[PDB]
Amino acid sequence: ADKELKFLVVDDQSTMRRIVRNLLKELGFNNVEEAEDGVDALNKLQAGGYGFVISDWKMPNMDGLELLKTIRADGAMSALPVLMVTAYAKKENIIAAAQAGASGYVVKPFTAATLEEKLNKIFEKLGM
Ligand code: BEF
Ligand SMILES: [Mn+2]
């Protein structure tokens, strides 16, 4: 994918946002911004330029399932890639996110290899 692709990394825990941003850097992506919940995320997204979202689920203000649903319903960003990265491992959580339009789903804790593989899976799917 284009190394100038702009990422928004969304999670209410700074430790996890820091993990993801550093992994992206290693993969060659330095155009990376952060958001602390789905409301903060939407404000950043509305400001423009984003080409990929990596998002937690459990967050205050607006959770990641609601964020994914909002993105997918909005005409301006309906096909924006959204990778869910979350501690929720139950099949019903994976179903709800998949059915809501998740581009992919990674369960915490995850390895560096897993994040790279699932990102690449999405790039290939979208021809990026
Ligand atoms: F809080 Be996230 F769903 F891991
Ligand atoms: Mn969380």
Image: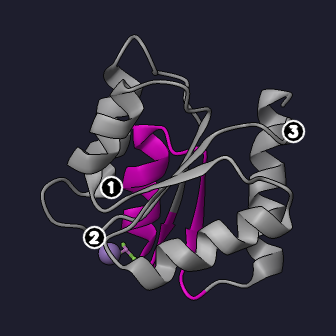
Does 124 sit above or below residue 55? Answer: above
Question: SS at mark 2?
Answer: loop
Q: How is the image coloured?
A: one colour
Q: Which mark is residue 1?
A: 3
Asked whether mark 2 and ligand 1 are closer than 8 Å, the reply comes as yes
Residue in view at x 87 percent, y 39 percent: 1
* Residue 92 placement: quadrant: bottom left
Does 37 sit above or below residue 69? Answer: below
| 3D distance between C-alphas at marks 1 and 2 | 7 Å
The residue that mark 1 highlights is: 64
**Does the magenta segment cover residue 82?**
no
* In this picture, residue 10 sits left or right of residue 67: right
Asked whether mark 1 and ligand 1 are closer than 8 Å, the reply comes as yes
Q: Residue furthest bottom?
A: 109
Q: Amino acid at mark 3?
A: Ala
Residue in view at x 77 percent, y 53 percent: 29
Which dot, 1 or 3, sits closer to the camera? 3
Label 2–label 3 contact, CB within 8 A: no
Q: Say whether disc 1 or disc 3 marks the residue closer to the N-terminus.
A: 3
Please state the extent of the stretch shown in magenta in the rendering: 85-109
Q: Amino acid at mark 2?
A: Lys
Residue 120 in picture, x, y percent from top left: 84, 52
Question: SS at mark 3?
Answer: loop
Residue 31 in picture, x, y percent from top left: 67, 46
Residue in view at x 51 percent, y 45 percent: 102
* In this picture, residue 72 sits left or right of residue 119: left
Q: Say whether disc 2 or disc 3 marks the residue closer to the N-terminus.
A: 3
Residue 86 in picture, x, y percent from top left: 45, 72
The residue that mark 2 highlights is: 58
